Length: 614
Ligand SMILES: O=C(Nc1ccnc(Cl)c1)Nc1ccnc(C#Cc2cccc(C(=O)O)c2)c1
Image (cartoon, rainbow, N blue to C red; front, side, top):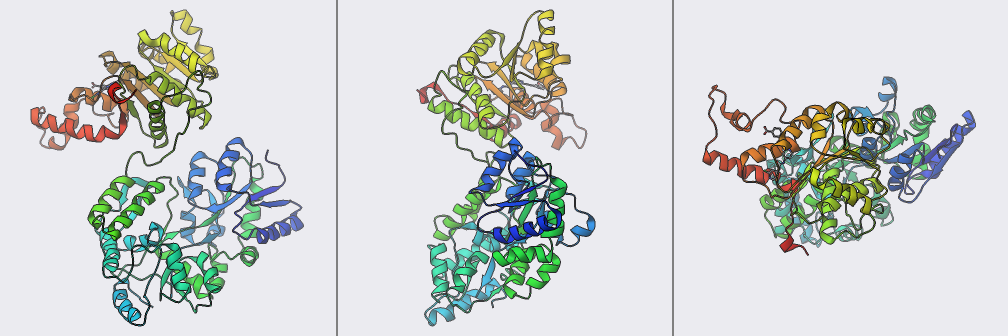
């Protein structure tokens, strides 16, 4: 479990773990509290597993970005340092450990990419290579294949990953396509076509070139310094050049110390971190085992700044931007990796490659999660290839906080595909919470039966019967002992005073073949009185070319957005109602509205036909 009156700390093997242990020994010496320092293999991967249990370490040491995921799950505690302690650390480092307006960790170290040799501007480098190539060398050689290294000039003029709003990042405000991003990336390909730089240059080539004295400059980080020290090159470290009178913005990696929320030793971790480790002597002890580069502590940074290399990694960091703590970043990197490659290799123009990457980073199904096999709780049958493909798309809906439509033709096992989602959300996620399933009366008994065949594990209630029979089910609900609740549309409408009181995790409505008039009265109640974030619709029809049906589908998928607006006429006339004119849509206007809604809903519907399956 998680032992009281003691401290267990996890830090990576590539860090000053033995140095940190001495700070722990000094803590035990003065207080009596034992401090255990461990470096487990893939600790960033083991931490979310053990912390969800209520086990693992009291303190975790990792970069602030991975801490964003843990903070969302609620695995890390809201740290409570006084104003006076916060004033000791650089204010920007606290922003790296802020999640939903809460300090979730104590910043330790700081890392950013640096210019290693100087050219004050990027613009002055084409000239410099002319000289160096006459002498038999090259002015610059860095890893181009990876977007982490190429990004600082792209971000310089105006480029950005996600726009940082008041407190949070916007995963829809992506700046891979603006004037700035294009200006920077055009300059990069300019240098490639002028033969100053080669597009085939990777990490191994860029490194071996600077070490063998073949190139005058390179862009890397502190991790390289060790391998260049052993190369006897008279290298220096400075700030990255200014593009268009604006500085280059590299990504800032802040080593942080996070407190586990399952730990009974929270005040002990505050005392050890604030008073033993986040001190000049405390950081110095770690820095002696394995250097920390720049540090968040003003006092110890001013002293380390005597070394120009450390004052450099700190100049770059203050001028750059901190790495976003959100999982959407994986889609942004996979976008800009291929964007930069294609542009430079000539396979796409700058304006083309960036257009795609901007579309791909802002895509709804940003977070990817492979589904190889089905859930263990799903037995007495094996899910077909398209049915597994359907489970992967439905988990992607849950992962990216999207509502969706499974419009597969009747008899494609939508029922089994739904059942398979619930089982995977229990096996691989801790989502056992109440599931609402609204089915047609005709197939109610087939749903209760299919659950019995495929997932006997899943304890379900069947909200059906005479008034007295339903009143009998009331206590089992209040317990929350159940996993699923199956019912017809009439009991959602009639027995709202009992069913609306539950905090439904996921909610599923199966309309069968076609939707009916009573499906809208059902959603009118569902929207007003019921609480369910995630929603899924099971239909047999494809996306209709009728505005009333699309209006309905919209109110089912986005219940919040259509509060004040009752009709599609009021909704789509809104940009034209400034004069108080009341005119309905016409044939043409309506065709274009249908067209746009089909484009808008495209990533929320999954349909397969029988002729393309088998
Ligand atoms: O729309 C659907 N299926 C579907 C299937 C294939 N293509 C299309 Cl376009 C649609 N199903 C469907 C299932 C359940 N509840 C609704 C609804 C509604 C609603 C809520 C509030 C106000 C109004 C209103 O009418 O003011 C309507 C729609």
